[PDB]
Image (cartoon, coloured by chain):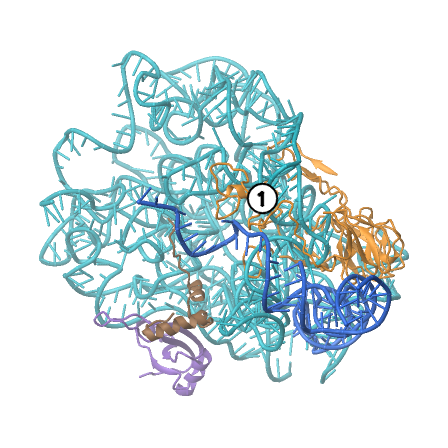
Chain colours: A brown, B purple, C orange, D blue, E cyan
RNA sequence: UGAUAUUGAAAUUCGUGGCUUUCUAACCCGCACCACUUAUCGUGGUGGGAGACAGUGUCAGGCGGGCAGUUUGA
RNA sequence: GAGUAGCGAAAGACGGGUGAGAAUCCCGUCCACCGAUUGACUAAGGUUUCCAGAGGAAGGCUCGUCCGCUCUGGGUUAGUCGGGUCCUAAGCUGAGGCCGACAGGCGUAGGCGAUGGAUAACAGGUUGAUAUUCCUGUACCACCUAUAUCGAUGGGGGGACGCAGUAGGAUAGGCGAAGCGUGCGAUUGGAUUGCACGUCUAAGCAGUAAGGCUGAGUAUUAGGCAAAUCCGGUACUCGGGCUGAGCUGUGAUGGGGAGAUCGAGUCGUUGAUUUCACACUGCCGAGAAAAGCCUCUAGAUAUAGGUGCCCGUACCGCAAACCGACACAGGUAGUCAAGAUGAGAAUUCUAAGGUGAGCGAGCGAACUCUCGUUAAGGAACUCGGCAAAAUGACCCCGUAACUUCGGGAGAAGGGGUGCUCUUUAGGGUUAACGCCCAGAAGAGCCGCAGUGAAUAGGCCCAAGCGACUGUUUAUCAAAAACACAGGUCUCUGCUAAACCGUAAGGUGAUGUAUAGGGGCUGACGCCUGCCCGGUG
């Protein structure tokens, strides 16, 4: 059976990722939130 | 510069077989070209270079008590000589 | 005329088709083509705003001359051609300068004969000229609506209108739908009827031949659920259990008029007919 | 669908008020040409078309399972 | 619960060796299994699993001396391969701009963006681990220096394109040879051209090459935002260019070989799903863009040595390295693909190559599963012929109603099919012999049986429904439900109705009443009666 999640390096970085996040006002809110929690990776 | 370009020579089985010919191996700075590695080997050793091949190597996993950690990333360059020899000893 | 097929297959049982005997060449003039990528009923936002549009055959746009501008310079018809984007055929007319451009082909122009534009031409098929210079009782086509803009009325296969009267600066005319209306006298028109009069008697024949044209299937509202259509719901088959039939957005859709009041053309139209 | 603001002009008409006409200066044109300009955006100029209408704000009446919140005894 | 269930599709055996310990590790022989794949490549994805030494705690459904596991040392080399320093599509962004309580939405010039266009390298050797990258040999491309031309930021040409169909030219590959090389020659009754293998080598250069396309000159000028000798028109005379697979040379005097430092590389025939090539013919559904490239003018002033950057390159890749929590009977684009048999890429057996399945040894109870056979009967079984059985290929003779004249039709129903020997008509290629491909008639021989195995429709009669191909409840429903071609009503005159959105902007549509949106009906045939009081 085909499963969800067929991985894809370039799709992964265009939908989730630093520049995509820093493009929207709500994406910068995600990254602010993860910084005050102290996550080791932000995106 | 020209001593920032070159870091240290490599001494293994595959490199001692290469200087049976006139091929010498160094570990260089990770941010330089072929054409800088070529113009730095004559300024230091005073030889005449015929070619330079470069390789980028990626960081390797390495544990000490099953830990995290990666080695440095490396850039090693094989230079061919037309005139002379490098006695790196 | 209309090529009729033998019933070799159930698909081609009652299926007809044009014979294409008027089309003189079978390849466009390369310097007059644009791309035409499909926009299949989807707008800015990317949402389907018009139903039943989809993926057909690929097409290139040909640049048609709807405002006939080159006046007092003759043009010889070089070729009649096929256009995928409209229901009429098109003609390639070469000017006396060496300037080629397409024209909508009228019902009775053959390859070779000449045409011309401007307010000093002959009243014969293929010519264009303002509406103050057309004698009452002529059938025209490709009728402008604002001067300089280009023709907009009577551009389908077999379409025409005829001039009726004259006011001070306007002109009476009856359209293909029987509505009577006055148009400004400075707006041009072409003499004749649009060709391809047998385009309507074609019997498509297959479901898959309407998928080649870009039409996608229609689900009747009766066989939907109540969250989809006002006509949805019910035991088995149901009648339209409402005073009037409704559209998929809940407006009345049989007899109820939708033209909006306070329009600037409320003066210009005389006799109405849909 | 009305009143009213943006909103002006001259006349005819029957009772200083209304009605209807006509005019154009306001407003409008997904309209032609010319600049910015490499530009099917925009802004400005020029001809044309329409014009005190339309569009827009406030107030008012109709319609309104298209869409909401709910009630539907012991 | 309990020393219980299970231990995940499939064949192993023995000998020798290593070790404290061997069904399980390494070497050998034989046997088996896949082979349009259990073989060879390569995208994606994964990230060191790759290689060599060493180890046996845990992981491995058993064991382990072994490992994709642990330990410490290594391994990826490019002017030409693929990507950037080149082009653009859908989309994504967008100076100024337009819109909006805020936040922001939209959009112009202009940019980003391959799954497409452009673009200069080949053969052989070599490592434990890389190679069109290193080495040997022979090349080609851009630039730089020594020894009129350049030319648009602009114009034109080009680039530049669908689907189907058949015929042809080649070549790769296969096959056969008393063509010639090499290397054997039998201890089971026989035989001795008798048995096995081999039978060639690029890019580049410079030659000629089936086929495919198609008038060429001169003058002229109201067009291509200015210009033009270029293009597009017009009038005149007169009726060889530019592309293209292959082949030959010569490379290179070398390189590789069946093999014993030496060593052959001929002839015939079958031939593509590759190439000439979307060429040619036909059809209607009418089949990207941009740069490189070639010209035009606004304008402007032939050998000798060198130089050539960045990123990827290991290994798995129908799999124990990827997605499925697992060393999981599932899923995972593309290229290559031999012999016998055949229409075949089907079937059965084999090649090149790979593999023997990470628990076993016994015994041969019930009962469960998967498979084979069955007296006499032959649907009596059962809700129901469910399941099983039977049919099955090629050839020939034959074939009903009904029909929309196409069908029904492989209707039904019958007969043939192995091998040997005679004689007999031709058709591919060649000067012949040859070498392939097919037929007809006769006379025999064997068996229970001759598509002797494997793979390959059961038929008929009548009734309801839906015309038909098609679509659907991923994971209890595939249908009489949905589509549909056709029919009908209605709304809509263009800044159209309709629809998305606060608007701006859009779809409709670069369309214009033979057009578009919505409601119902549902091929085709013959038809569709009455009622406008109530509601719209």
Quarter of the image for the N terminus of chain C: give it.
Answer: top right
Camera-side residue of C27 and A35 = A35
Find residue E10 and report its horizontal and vertical position in percent. 26, 41
Camera-side residue of E463 and E117 = E463
Image height check: is C7 above or below E359?
Answer: above
Quadrant of residue C35 in the image? bottom right
- The residue lying at 61 percent from left, 42 percent from top is C209
Subunit bearing disc 1: C
Image height check: is E412 above or below C205?
Answer: above
Find residue E222 and report its horizontal and vertical position in percent. 85, 66
Compared across the picture, whether E529 is left or right of E86 comes to right
Compared across the picture, whether E337 is left or right of D8 comes to left
Quadrant of residue E433 in the image? top right
User: What is the tally of numbered marks visible in this picture?
Assistant: 1
Image height check: is D33 above or below C21?
Answer: below
Q: Is residue C206 visible?
A: no
- The residue lying at 54 percent from left, 57 percent from top is C47
Camera-side residue of C48 and A20 = C48
Q: Is residue B85 visible?
A: yes
- The residue lying at 65 percent from left, 45 percent from top is C255
Find residue A38 and report its horizontal and vertical position in percent. 32, 74
Compared across the picture, whether E487 is left or right of E368 comes to right
Image height check: is E130 above or below C54?
Answer: below
Say which residue label 1 marks: C245
Find residue E357 and report its horizontal and vertical position in percent. 25, 47
Element at badge 1? loop
Quadrant of residue E4 in the image? top left
């Amino acid at each position: 059976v085909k499963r969800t999640y067929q991985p894809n390096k370039r799709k992964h970085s265009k939908v989730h990722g630093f520049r995509k996040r820093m493009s929207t006002k709500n994406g910068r809110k995600v990254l602010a939130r993860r910084r005050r929690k102290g996550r080791k990776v932000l995106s | 510069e020209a001593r920032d370009i070159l870091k240290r020579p490599v001494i293994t089985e595959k490199s001692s077989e290469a200087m049976a010919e006139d091929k010498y191996t160094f570990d260089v700075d990770t941010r330089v070209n072929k054409t800088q590695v070529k113009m730095a080997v004559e300024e230091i050793f005073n030889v005449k270079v015929a070619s330079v091949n470069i390789m980028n190597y990626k960081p390797k996993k390495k544990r000490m008590g099953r830990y995290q950690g990666y080695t440095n990333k490396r850039r090693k360059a094989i230079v061919t000589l037309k005139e002379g020899s490098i006695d790196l000893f | 005329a209309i090529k009729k097929y033998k019933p070799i297959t159930n698909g081609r049982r009652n299926m007809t088709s044009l014979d294409f005997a008027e089309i003189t060449k079978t390849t466009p003039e390369k310097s007059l083509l644009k791309p035409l990528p499909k926009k299949a009923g989807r707008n800015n936002q990317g949402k389907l705003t018009v139903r039943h549009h989809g993926g057909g055959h690929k097409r290139q746009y040909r640049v048609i001359d709807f405002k006939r501008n080159k006046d007092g310079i003759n043009a010889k018809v070089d070729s009649i051609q096929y256009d995928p984007n409209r229901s009429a055929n098109i003609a390639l007319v070469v000017y006396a300068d060496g300037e080629k451009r397409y024209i909508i082909a009228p019902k009775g122009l053959e390859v070779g004969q000449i045409v011309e534009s401007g307010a000093e031409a002959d009243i014969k098929v293929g010519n264009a000229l303002p509406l103050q210079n057309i004698p009452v009782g002529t059938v025209v086509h490709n009728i402008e609506l604002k001067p300089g803009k280009g023709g907009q009325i009577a551009r389908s296969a077999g379409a025409s209108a005829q001039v009726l009267g004259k006011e001070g600066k306007y002109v009476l005319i009856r359209l293909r739908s029987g509505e009577v209306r006055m148009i400004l006298s400075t707006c041009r028109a072409t003499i004749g009827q649009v060709g391809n009069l047998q385009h309507e008697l074609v019997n498509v024949g297959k479901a898959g031949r309407s998928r080649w044209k870009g039409i996608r299937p229609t689900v009747r509202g009766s066989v939907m659920n109540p969250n989809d259509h006002p006509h949805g719901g019910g035991e088995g088959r149901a009648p339209i259990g409402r005073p009037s039939p409704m559209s998929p957005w809940g407006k009345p859709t049989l007899g109820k008029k939708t033209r909006r009041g306070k329009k600037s053309s409320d003066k210009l139209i005389v006799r109405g007919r849909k």
